[PDB]
Amino acid sequence: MITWGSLLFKGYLKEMDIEYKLFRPDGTPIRAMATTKIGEFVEEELRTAQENNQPD
Amino acid sequence: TYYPPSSFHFLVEFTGIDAKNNDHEFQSVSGLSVDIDTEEFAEGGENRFKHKFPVKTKYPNLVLKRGVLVDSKVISWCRDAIEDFEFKPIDLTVKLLNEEHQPLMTWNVVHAYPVKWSVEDFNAQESKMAIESVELSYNYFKTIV
Image (tube, rainbow over all chains, first blue to last red; front, side, top):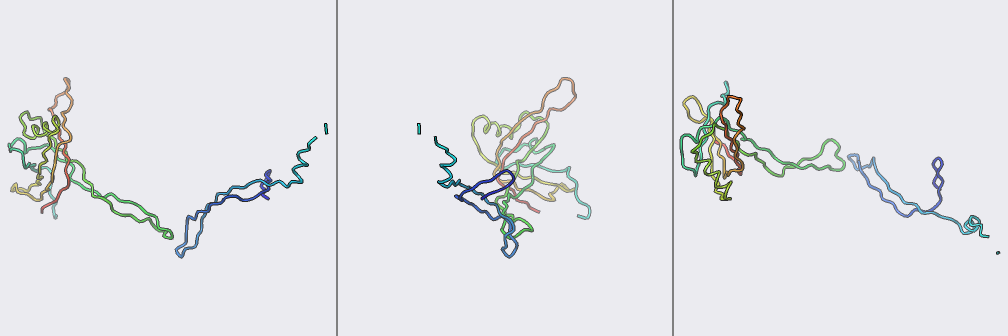
């Protein structure tokens, strides 16, 4: 679950890349950048309640 | 030196072109310098500086100026290259002279050929001398001193 302000999103990780940029002289990293992609999850009992499907 | 020399007394000589005294006299000479191209590299963990490496030695063109001379041998040589693509490189010597008119120091210019020739604009309202300019490409130079 991902929350920030107005945002609220549920799902799964699909992809990630991490790149290491700066280092201390003994090889300890102090800066890195990450790119992320998230998919969306709906449980099947909640899908039929949101699609309130109504001659029947 | 203790008293360094001045720069207004010098001689330009050509090898491979018939000599005439009027082709050894010039108003100005420029381009006797050199530089080294480099590349940079950042090594992870080293934050005090980047590394620099040499790649190539580089030389600028040699530029000569003088008042216009109509029967020059150097210009005939320039024209063969300019008009017909006939190229025949020459060697050249630049001499910086002392008070006995002997060399203090010389420059040996190797395998030169013409890339440019021009004459400055005419102006009916100004009192001026017609000035000619010649530029040469070469491979490298050495010094003797």
